[PDB]
Length: 188
RNA sequence: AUUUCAAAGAAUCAUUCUUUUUAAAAUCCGAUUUUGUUACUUUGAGUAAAUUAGAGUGUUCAAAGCAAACAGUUAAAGCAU
Image (cartoon, rainbow, N blue to C red; front, side, top):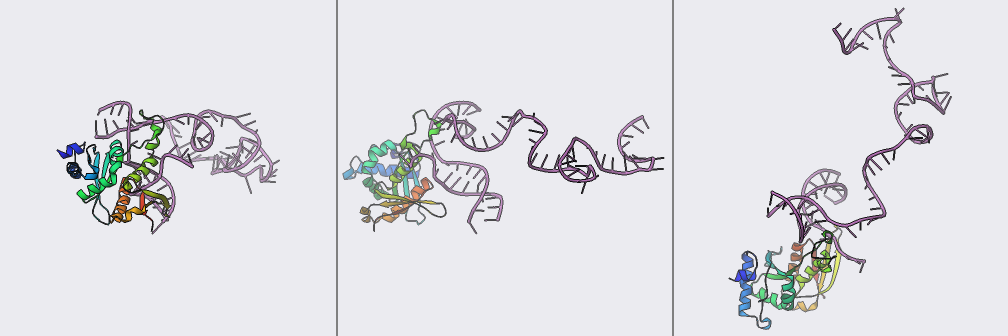
């Protein structure tokens, strides 16, 4: 039924809930984003819980090609619709291969810039904020030798009441994905 | 300018030394083991002595030498039948 259609692999409970929700959104149709999710196929879904315990956040992995072509174009409205349907905080990300060019893999000449560790990690930072847009990045090196990514967003999100819970969620999600701490801010 | 950041453990006096894991391809029995060239650097191999540094060693000391030291009035010990 819904789960096999949305998720290619054998599906867990929250993967099946996402599949059900996504099918229900497509079937019901959200008027401005009509043809809502027909092209979508999912790789995986993951559940992450903030230390502050302001609900839960869901990370969803999507193929780069599907993500770029479909998801990116409607993403803020799409995530808001997914959030409205299931109240846990959703993030949509592209899976991206990261390549060590030392090994000389058959399918690539040289080193692609898109597959560099740094480019992918910056791209994943872009994916998590994606409905909102970065004004500037600044990396603070604290005295412990930890490095902290201070990410400035734009001033349009002062309308959104979910702001702080999403900022903590972005920090948590990035921290789970790789061992980089973020902090967030926006103009006064 | 530019391209793989890091994380956690253990040993040790919020420091220090050490170990584990975190993409992809090829290969072998879900797992097992490999992945640009050079500069630079690390260990090494193979190095004639005399000299030189430098140990051993009271040439009567020292420059030296490569020797010496030990027991025993004119013997025991040791190992051999």
